Amino acid sequence: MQRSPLEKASVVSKLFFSWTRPILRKGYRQRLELSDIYQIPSVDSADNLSEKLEREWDRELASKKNPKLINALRRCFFWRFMFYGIFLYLGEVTKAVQPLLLGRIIASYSIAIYLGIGLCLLFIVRTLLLHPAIFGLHHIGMQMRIAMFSLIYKKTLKLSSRVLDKISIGQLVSLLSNNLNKFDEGLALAHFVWIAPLQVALLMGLIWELLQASAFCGLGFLIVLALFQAGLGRMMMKYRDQRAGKISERLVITSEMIENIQSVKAYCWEEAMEKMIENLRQTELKLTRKAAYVRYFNSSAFFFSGFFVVFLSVLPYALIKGIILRKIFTTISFCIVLRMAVTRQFPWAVQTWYDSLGAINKIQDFLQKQEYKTLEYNLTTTEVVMENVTAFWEEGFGGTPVLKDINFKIERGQLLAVAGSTGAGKTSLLMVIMGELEPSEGKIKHSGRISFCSQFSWIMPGTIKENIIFGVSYDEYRYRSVIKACQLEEDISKFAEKDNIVLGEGGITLSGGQRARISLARAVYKDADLYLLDSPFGYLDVLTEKEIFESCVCKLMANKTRILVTSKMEHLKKADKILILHEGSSYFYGTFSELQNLTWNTYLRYITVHKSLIFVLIWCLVIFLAEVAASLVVLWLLGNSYAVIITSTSSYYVFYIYVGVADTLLAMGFFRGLPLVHTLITVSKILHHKMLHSVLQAPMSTLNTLKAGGILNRFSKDIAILDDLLPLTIFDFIQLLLIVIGAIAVVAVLQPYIFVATVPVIVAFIMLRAYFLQTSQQLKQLESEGRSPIFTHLVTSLKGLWTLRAFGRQPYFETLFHKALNLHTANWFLYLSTLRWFQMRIEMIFVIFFIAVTFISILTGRVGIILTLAMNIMSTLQWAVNSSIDVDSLMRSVSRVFKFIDMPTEGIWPSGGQMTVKDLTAKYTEGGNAILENISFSISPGQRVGLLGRTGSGKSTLLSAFLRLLNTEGEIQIDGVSWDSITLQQWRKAFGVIPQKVFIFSGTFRKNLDPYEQWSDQEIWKVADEVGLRSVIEQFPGKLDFVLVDGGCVLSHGHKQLMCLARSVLSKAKILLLDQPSAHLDPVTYQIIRRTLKQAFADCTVILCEHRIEAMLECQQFLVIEENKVRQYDSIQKLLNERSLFRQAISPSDRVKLFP
Ligand SMILES: Nc1ncnc2c1ncn2[C@@H]1O[C@H](COP(=O)(O)OP(=O)(O)OP(=O)(O)O)[C@@H](O)[C@H]1O
Ligand SMILES: Nc1ncnc2c1ncn2[C@@H]1O[C@H](COP(=O)(O)OP(=O)(O)OP(=O)(O)O)[C@@H](O)[C@H]1O
Ligand SMILES: CC(C)CCC[C@@H](C)[C@H]1CC[C@H]2[C@@H]3CC=C4C[C@@H](O)CC[C@]4(C)[C@H]3CC[C@]12C
Ligand SMILES: CC(C)CCC[C@@H](C)[C@H]1CC[C@H]2[C@@H]3CC=C4C[C@@H](O)CC[C@]4(C)[C@H]3CC[C@]12C
Ligand SMILES: O=C(O)c1ccc(/C=C2\SC(=S)N(c3cccc(C(F)(F)F)c3)C2=O)cc1
Ligand SMILES: [Mg+2]
Ligand SMILES: [Mg+2]
C-alpha cells in the first residue's frame, strides 16, 4: 500500500491532475492488482474526522438550548465551502461574457483579430477555474459523510434496550445507503442557489443592451416556468416519503428469509416468501412510477422553452418597430445561457439543499435518542444483593411485572442455582442483574466486573481463537487451560487449520453444541468478579455436560462468584444457594437442606429483457427520422414592418435562426418520454423477481459462501439505481444523442466545412472515452464491492449488542468499523480523481480545436455566424460525452444483478412410511472430507427410531442427507420409490421436519404458523391448545393478530420450541424428522412433547434425535453415530451395557426409569 502520490505532487501536477497518469497506464494494459491501490491521505482518516466532529457537536449540545448539527458542520467546513464557491462563480461569469464577444464579432462582419484572441483566452481561464474548484467541493462532501457515519455508529452501541426494539436493521441500512455516494457529489451543485440569480441579473443587463424592455416578456415566461418546476419538486418529495417505510420493511423480511434459507428449503416455503416480497414490491412500484412521471416533466423544461423564450423576447420589439434578423440571431446565444440557468441549475440546487437538510435532520433525530445507564461500587464486598426487586418489560405498564419482589444474596466464591419452568423469568432476572432491564422497585448492588454467556450463542467473523480472545492479549497458559476444560480439543483437532479456521458470522459451519461451547469458552477466558450463565449445557449430551460442569464450573472457577441457570438435580446438589421462581414470583429461596426438608453484452441483455422497450425505442427512432425529413423539406422550401428581410442582405440569416431552434425542434414530447420511463421501470420489476427466485433456488454449497452484508448490498443499492436513477439518466442521454445527430445532418448541407470539421472532434472524444473506461470500470467495480464489509460489520454488531456491552469491547468494535470505512474511502477517492482527469482532458481538446478553427476563420462575413454554430455543436457534444460516462457508471449495477441471476440451480406414495438406505455417503463440499461414510440400514413402517451420538458427530448431517440438502451419494428409498425417480419437490413434500434452528419471521402469529393460508382459525386454535400455546398467545393485545418483530423477541426459548412443534403438528406427513425438539425444556414441559408424540403421530414413522434420556424410553429402534459410522441397536439397555462412561453419567432418576 504505497503512500498517496498526491502527497509529494507539485503545484502544477496537482492543478492538472497529472499524478493519476500511472494508475491509468497500468489499468489500460493489465488487470489491476492489489499493489496498485494507494493509501488514503492522512486528512481523510475516519479516526481524526470523527474526533473533530465529535468535539464540535459535544460543544453544541451543552452550549445551546436548541442544538443543531448544522452549526457543528458549519464550524468544521464553512470557510473551505465558501473558498471554493468564489472560484466557481468566477468561472461561471466567463460563460456569460462569451456571447457578448461573439455578437461583437458578428456585428463587425483589424478589430476582429483582437476579438478572437480575447475570446480564445476566455476558454483557458474557464478550464483552470471550474475543474479544480469542483473537485475541492467533492472532497468536502466526502469528508462530511465519513464523519457523520462515524458518529452514527458510536451512538448505536449506546442505545437503550427499550428503544432498540423499535429501530430495525432495515431502517439502519437504508439510512446509510441513501447518502453513500449521493451526499458526496451533491456539494458541487449547492452554490448555484445564489450563483444563478446573479447570472440572471448580468444576462438581463446584457439583453437590455439589445432589446431594451422587451426582454422582460421572456423573463416573465421563465419566471412562470420556474414556479411550475417548484410545484413539480414539491409534488416529487411527497411520494418518496410514502415509499421509505415500505422499502425498510422489505429489506427486513428479505434479510431474515436469506438468513434462514435451510429452514425455508426444509419447509418448502419458497413460494410463500416470494409472494410476500411481490406484495410489498407492488406498493413500492406504484409510488416509484408516479415520481418518475413527475420527474420527466421536470427534466423536459429546458428543451421545450428554447423557441418560446426567443420568440417572446423579440415579439414586442418587432410589433412596435421593424427588427433586423441579425438581432434575432444574436438573441439566441444569450437565451441559451439564461434558460440553462433558470430551468436546470437553480432547481437542481434547490432540490440538493432540500435533500441534504432532510438527511442531516434525520441524523440529528437519531443522535438524540435514549441511552443505556447503570451503577456499581468499587468498594463493595464482591457480593451480589437483590432487595425486593420488581421489573416491568414494558415501560408504559410499569400491567403484570415479569419479576416481583425477587430477593437473593451471595458472598464471593459461592454458586447460586436458578431453577424454574418456561417463562418464569430466569433470562429476565439475568437481564435485570446486567442492567439491561431497569427495575420499577428495588435496588441491585454488586461490583461492575461481570462475564456473560447468553442462552442464544453469538459468533463473529474470524478464527475460533479470535472469538475466544475477543480483543485482549493472548495468554498461552490460560487459553490452553480453558480449551482443555471446555472439551474443545477433540472437535478442534478435526479442523484442517485447528482453531485458525475462519468462522462465518453466526457459526454457520458449526454444530449447536460446538457454538455453545465456544461461547462458554469465551466467557470462561475473560476474568471477572461475577459470572452469569444461561443454560450452557443445553445443546450438549450427558457425558459432555457432566465433564464440563465438573472441570469448568466446580474446578476451574472455584473462587469466583457465580450464577447458573439449571433444572438438573445433580447441579442443584452442589449449589450453595437455590432460587426457585414460578411466574415471576419467588417460590423458594434457600439451601438444598431446606428444599429436601420441604462489455456490450450487458447493454444487449438489458435492452432485450422486455419487448415493450424495443417497441418504444423503435417508435422514438421512427419519429426522429420523420422530424429530420420534415426539417429538410422545410429548409428546401425556404431555399426555393413586422420583420425586415432583404434579398440583398440578411436573407441568409433565416436558415441560421432555424438551426438555432433545433433544441426545441428535436425535443421528445410526452408521447415518447413517458412510455420510455414506464417501460424501463417495468424492466426493473422483472429483474428483481428473477434475482430473488434464483437466490432461493440455489444450492446450499453456493449459498454458504455469501456474506449478509453483500446480499444486503445487492438487494438495497443495486435495485434502487435501476428503479430510480437509471430510467432518467437514459432519457437524458437519448435526448442529447438525438439532438446532436439531427443537428449534424442539417448543418452539413448549409455549410459543408462545419461537417468536415465536427468529425475530427468526435473521433478524438471517442478515442479518449475508450481509453478512460478500461480503468474506470475496474475502479467502479472495486468501489461497488467496498460497501459489503461496512454492511456486514453493522449487521454483526447489531446482533451482538448485549454481549458487547456486557464485556466492554466498544472501543475494539469502533476501531474495526473505522478500518472498513477507510477501505471504502481509498477506492472512492481514486475513482473520483480519475473522473476529474478525464473531464479536464475533454475540455482541453475542445479548447485546442476551437482555437484552431477561430484563427483559421479569422485568417480566411459569415465567420461569426459559423463560429456561433460551431460552438453550439461542440458544447452539445461535450454534454453528451459526459452523459455517456454517467450511464456507463450506472450500468455496473445491472452487471452485478445479472451475475447474481446467473447462479446454478440446486437440482398415495407416502403410505407405510417404510425407508431403506444403501451405501450412503455425505459431504458438504466436493473434494472434501466425508462426514458420513458407508451408511446402510432399514426402518419398518410405523416405527420409532432414536438417533444418538456425542455433540458434533453428524446427527444433523444425517438428517440433512435424508432431505438431500448437501452432497449425497447412495440410494434412499421410501415405500419402494427411489429419490432419483421423482423430482426434489416431490421427495421433500413427504417429510415433516423440525429444525434445530428455530425460524421466526416478522409477521402475525397466524402467518408465522401458516404462511400459505390454508388452515382455518378454528383448527389453528385447536392445535395451539393441543401444544399449550393458548395462554401464551392470549397474553398479547392481538390474539393471532399480534405482529412479532425481531424474530420473536417477545417470546421465550421454550415458546419458540412449542411454535415449531405446532407447525409440525399442523403438517400431516407420514415420515417425521425431529431434531432435538426439547432443547432447553424442563421435565414438566417435556410432558407436552411426550403426549404429542404418542397422540398426534399415532400412525407415522418417527426418527427422533434427542440428548434427553427419558425420550429414549419412547423408541424401539436405535441408531448410534460413532467415528463416521452408524451402528444399529434394538434395546437401549443392550446399548448402555456396552458403554461404561455413558452409563455412569446417567442420572439416578434416568437409571431408575431404565432399570426398574
Ligand atoms: N423482550 C421482551 N419483551 C416483552 N416480554 C418479554 C420479552 N422477553 C421475554 N418476555 C416475556 O417475559 C416472560 C419471561 O420470559 P423469559 O425469557 O425470562 O423466560 P425464561 O424463564 O428464561 O424461559 P426459558 O426457560 O424458555 O428460557 C415470558 O412470558 C416472555 O414472553
Ligand atoms: N456447513 C458445514 N460445512 C462444513 N462442516 C460442517 C457444516 N455443518 C456442520 N459441519 C461439521 O459437521 C460435523 C457434524 O455436525 P452436526 O451438526 O451434524 O453435528 P451433531 O452431531 O448434530 O451435533 P449437535 O449435537 O451439536 O447438534 C461437525 O464437525 C461440524 O463442524
Ligand atoms: C459593451 C458594453 C456596452 C457593455 C459592458 C457591460 C459591463 C457592465 C460588464 C462587462 C464585463 C462585466 C464583468 C465581467 C466579470 C466580472 C467578475 C465577476 O466576479 C463580477 C462581475 C464582473 C465584474 C462583471 C460586471 C459587469 C461587466 C463589467
Ligand atoms: C449581479 C451582477 C454580476 C450583475 C449586475 C448587472 C449589471 C452587469 C447591469 C445592470 C444594468 C446594466 C446596464 C444597463 C444599461 C446600459 C446602457 C447600454 O448603452 C450599455 C450597457 C449598460 C451600461 C448596461 C450594462 C450592464 C449593467 C450595468
Ligand atoms: O456546461 C455544460 O454542461 C453545458 C455547456 C454548454 C451546453 C450547450 C448546449 S446544450 C444544447 S441543446 N445546445 C444547442 C442549442 C442550439 C442548437 C444546438 C444544435 F442544434 F446545434 F445541436 C445545440 C447547446 O449549445 C450545454 C451544457
Ligand atoms: Mg431463558
Ligand atoms: Mg445438530
Image (spheres, grey):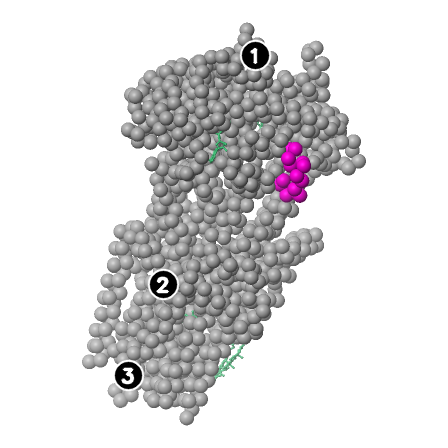
Q: Is mark 1 within 8 Å of ligand 2?
A: no
Q: Is residue 311 left or right of residue 20?
A: left
The quarter of the picture where the N terminus appears is bottom right
Instruction: Work out which residue is located at the far left of the displayed protein and give it.
Output: 640
Asked if the stretch drawn in magenta spans residue 881, the answer is no
Q: What is the secondary structure assignment of the residue under circle 2?
A: helix
Height in image: 1117 above or below 558?
A: above
Q: Residue at x 52, y 50 (%)?
A: 176
Q: CA distance from mark 3 to mark 1?
A: 113 Å
Instruction: Work out which residue is located at the far bottom of the displayed protein and give it.
Output: 110
Mark 3 — residue?
A: 652
Please, what is the three-letter code of the amino acid marked with disc 3?
Answer: Tyr
Mark 2 — residue?
A: 733
Q: Is residue 410 visible?
A: yes
Q: Which residues are magenta?
A: 469-482
Q: What is the secondary structure assignment of the residue under circle 3?
A: loop
Nearer the camera: disc 2 or disc 3: 2
Q: Residue at x 40, y 36 (%)?
A: 273
Q: Residues within 10 Å of mark 2 (few under 14, many from 20)?
A: some
Asked if the stretch drawn in magenta spans residue 470, the answer is yes
Please, what is the three-letter code of the amino acid marked with disc 1?
Answer: Arg
Q: What is the secondary structure assignment of the residue under circle 1?
A: helix
Q: Residue at x 71, y 17 (%)?
A: 591
* Position in image of residue 1137 (x %, y %): 53, 13
Mark 1 — residue?
A: 1151
Q: CA distance from mark 2 to mark 3?
A: 33 Å
